[PDB]
Image (cartoon, rainbow, N blue to C red):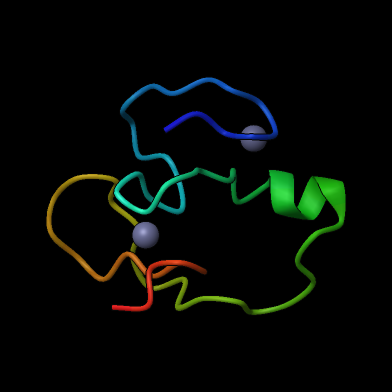
Length: 60
Ligand SMILES: [Zn+2]
Ligand SMILES: [Zn+2]
């Protein structure tokens, strides 16, 4: 799970997730000009403990 915009993982709680395929810092997408609005649930993240980690490829 290496941010295609940074390339550095940790554990704290990266986003969106890791299972998907790639990671994107909630700030990168905004710092790059990719997304421009509420493109998620912004209700909970957690890059581990079960949860509703939604993403572009997630779907779930
Ligand atoms: Zn990044
Ligand atoms: Zn995902």
